[PDB]
Image: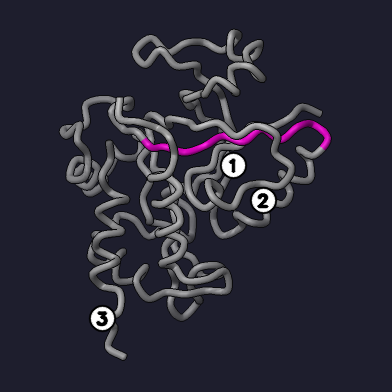
Amino acid sequence: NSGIWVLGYGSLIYKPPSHYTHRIPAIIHGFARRFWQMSTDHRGTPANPGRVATLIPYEDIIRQTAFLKNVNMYSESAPIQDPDDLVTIGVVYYIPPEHAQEVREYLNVREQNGYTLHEVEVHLETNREHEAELGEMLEQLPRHNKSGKRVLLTSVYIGTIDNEAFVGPETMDETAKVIAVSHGPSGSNYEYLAKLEQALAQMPIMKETDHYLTALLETVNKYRHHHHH
């Protein structure tokens, strides 16, 4: 078999697949990350479902007024004019052939709650070590005409707007109250958001932006420790 490239944009950024051998920062164009997937098994419960991350493609954004309004509200590029105006940061992992089959099965079970497997293009933000170890591969990837970055086809888990766990569109006030208090077998819903925002904030990817995630964390923090009990 071949190896696999797996894109992480939520908890896979800071709780990675097993056995990976490369981990590269990745610019995902044409998708917005939203906390519009409910979690009844990890970060919430059947009685009180949490919220976890999913990616919403441009082609779905432009099919509902509520989605288009929400992306413009939080984006510097408002009004969003084209798919490349939507930017989400993540990382891509390489799993070598010897482990790809087993890691795929682990990730399928880890993401069982409504995610499906897709293939998307990302722009790589490589460092010099990546360029030393993977230069022969990078030279064979196309360079994007606008960004000048190498473009890589990578697999990705996405809760599509059709899946049973999808709760979008949801206003930030409603999403933040749920994240502030939900808690499941994996831990608090708050930890999932806070670790994701920290893992992105601590990535050495500079400004060359969708403010949703930082706005969400700010709202969650205001609601935290102000529950009725």
In the picture as drawn, the residue positioned furthest to the front comes out as: 128
Asked if the residue at tag 3 contacts the one at tag 2, i.e. Cβ–Cβ closer than 8 Å, the answer is: no
Q: Nearer the viewer, mark 2 or mark 3?
A: 3
Mark 3 highlights which residue?
226
Which residue is painted at 19% across and 35% down in the image?
76
What's the magenta bit mostly, secondary-structure-wise?
strand
Q: Amino acid at mark 1?
A: Leu
Q: Is residue 112 left or right of residue 9?
A: right
Q: How many other residues sit within 10 Å of disc 3, few (<14), some (14-19) or many (≥20)? A: few
Q: CA distance from mark 2 to mark 3?
A: 36 Å
The magenta segment: 88-98
Disc on the earlier residue, 2 or 3: 2
Q: Is residue 227 left or right of residue 53?
A: left
Quadrant for the C terminus in the image: bottom left
Mark 2 highlights which residue?
108
Residue closest to the eye, 40 or 218 = 218
Q: Amino acid at mark 2?
A: Asn
Asked if the residue at tag 3 contacts the one at tag 1, i.e. Cβ–Cβ closer than 8 Å, the answer is: no
Quadrant for the N terminus in the image: top right
Where disc 1 sits, the SS reads: strand
Which residue is painted at 71% across and 44% down in the image?
104
Q: Position of residue 83 (x, y in %)?
A: 32, 27
Q: Position of residue 132 (x, y in %)?
A: 63, 16
Residue closest to the eye, 64 or 38 = 38
Which residue is painted at 30% across and 74% down in the image?
224
Residue 50 highlighted magenta (yes or no): no
Where disc 3 sits, the SS reads: loop
Asked if the residue at tag 2 contacts the one at tag 1, i.e. Cβ–Cβ closer than 8 Å, the answer is: yes
Disc on the earlier residue, 1 or 2: 2
Q: CA distance from mark 1 to mark 3?
A: 38 Å
Mark drawn on residue 117: 1
Q: Above or below — where is 78 with respect to 199?
A: above
